[PDB]
Amino acid sequence: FQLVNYTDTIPARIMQQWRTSDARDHTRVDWKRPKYTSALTYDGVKVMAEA
Amino acid sequence: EVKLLESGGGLVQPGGSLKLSCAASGFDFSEYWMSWVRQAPGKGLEWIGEINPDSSSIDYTPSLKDKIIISRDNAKKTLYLQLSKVRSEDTALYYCARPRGNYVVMDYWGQGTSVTVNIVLTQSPASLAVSLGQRATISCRASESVDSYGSSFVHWYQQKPGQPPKLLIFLASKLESGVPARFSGSGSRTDFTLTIDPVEADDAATYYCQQTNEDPYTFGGGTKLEIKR
Ligand SMILES: *[C@@H]1O[C@H](CO)[C@@H](O)[C@H](O)[C@H]1NC(C)=O
């Protein structure tokens, strides 16, 4: 099974924003071979923000 | 390790717009965004343009933004920068580079060429010379912090005149891949340091400490290294 679809509109836009941010201001550790727990964490932060 | 090709360095006519062929061979500029930097003779490099991987929106140099426009395409993996009102000092060595943030092997800048039409740091010692097999430790003092966003956010580019610059050490945790250099960022590094051991005739070049932790990435003065016979 596959939950994340990194080719759609919203996922690709979010990933492009993250890539621009990481180009300008580095993160702690890169996202080499992106997993799905990263997407779940992003969605959880968005859930807390929305609530 | 991605490979780049940049050829055609030649003068132009007064103001005659120019363009350089920066081909990203064996890879695509969608996995590592392509950025064009500009280094004059005997001076630190300057970011001429930062582009996007998905070919959505590119930037321009913070010095003269509207003065130049650099087009590029991910699938084509070929970029071309243009400008107008070309002056003498405007003819500086422009070089393409891939995004180093993806991997260490991705930090593979193009060849680079010149024509005849930030970051603050100081590396020491400026005049260094040791025989083959020696261990050299250069210290690059700075004014900003020594680590940004968890780990270190400084790098060291091993450039040579007319040769493609290479990024040996970066972020004190990811040294140059493919050809692992014995020198790399280490320790707390209040001043960026790398203990090259053992040196060789191939590892003799100008090491310049450019810290990405101080916006923007600007190559500093650096320290010279040779092969003392
Ligand atoms: C996932 O992305 C692909 C690529 O665009 C698309 O063809 C597919 O329809 C997407 N999945 C769903 C369920 O829409």
Image (tube, rainbow, N blue to C red):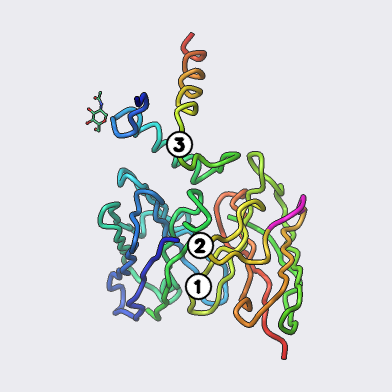
| Residue labelled with disc 1 | B40
Extreme residue toward the front, this view? A1
| Residue labelled with disc 3 | A34
Question: Looking at the image, is A42 positioned above or below residue B160?
Answer: above
Q: CA distance from mark 2 to mark 3?
A: 32 Å
Q: Are marks 1 and 2 in contact (CB under 8 Å)?
A: yes
Residue at the (60%, 39%) spot, across then down:
A28
Q: Secondary structure at mark 1?
A: loop
The chain under label 2 reads B
Q: CA distance from mark 1 to mark 3?
A: 38 Å
- Residue B49 lies, in percent from the top left, at 41, 56
Question: Callout 1: 10 Å neighbours few (<14), some, many (20+)?
Answer: some
| Residue labelled with disc 2 | B46
- Residue B39 lies, in percent from the top left, at 50, 69
What span is in magenta?
B185-189
Q: Secondary structure at mark 2?
A: strand
Three-letter amino acid code of the residue under disc 2: Glu
Three-letter amino acid code of the residue under disc 1: Ala
Are discs 1 and 2 located on one and the same chain?
A: yes
The chain under label 3 reads A
Q: Quadrant of ligand 1?
A: top left
Q: Is mark 1 within 8 Å of ligand 1?
A: no
Residue at the (73%, 79%) spot, across then down:
B133
Residue at the (46%, 64%) spot, across then down:
B109
Badge 1 or badge 2: first in the primary sequence = 1
